[PDB]
Length: 272
Ligand SMILES: CN1C(=O)c2sccc2N(C)c2nc(Nc3ccc(S(N)(=O)=O)cc3)ncc21
Image (cartoon, rainbow, N blue to C red; front, side, top):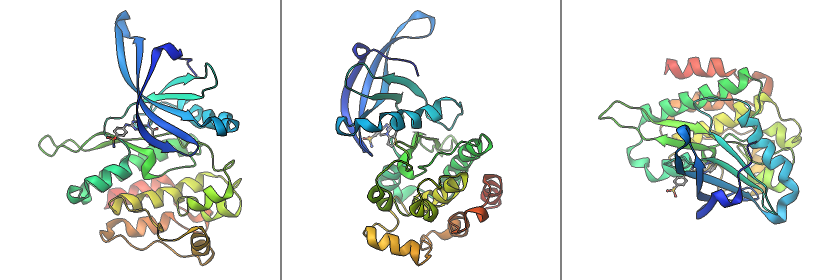
């Protein structure tokens, strides 16, 4: 990673939290192209000091995204570890996380918008699959909206997939159960069962989020009931706008070997 000086970073408003992390908007003073000074908006992810033991995992996640370059992957500017702090410095995406955006804009997000955003996420996951890189935490909160749909231009929305945060392979089991149904059944059984097929399951759950106006599947169920949901081999209910329901269910296959490749997922999406 590129090491960024603390003096060059300015923390501003809190933009929420991740697992064991606080997220902030920030400003980075930098020498840009042609040597001109800029103040660039950045996103700052701070690992909680009480959870500093996850430092490695915390950075590994983002490191995984940094070794590949792709239009649908969020950019990492680097890290600030000068001091007790563990700071990750990423690009600031203007319109924030997709789950929030889907909630706030639900009244005017239609089927074509959902299909375009699903195609983009599928394309990003296909890039990862082709590179045999496991994301491990595909969810609508980890999708960021770079630009909104502009029907006057014909411009579609454009999304980027963010880093997965601290790996489910090292997280406490109660946090893993709270993350049902994003975390696949096999990973509840064994978190070290982290595979490429994991991302197909989680992509299905994310599609459900995208089609459900930002609702959280199974949120009414506590941890015991989410566990039982997997034990009883249930599927999520079809969204009211059910045009993606079969794809959601084909991705959320309890048999990981039977989950479709992202090429087949993309061919389905195009067929819709
Ligand atoms: C880089 N990045 C992330 O990795 C993740 S992963 C899960 C959440 C994020 N976050 C917080 C982000 N929010 C943003 N920009 C942004 C813009 C507007 C708003 S809002 N809804 O307050 O107006 C929030 C975040 N830009 C980028 C991110």
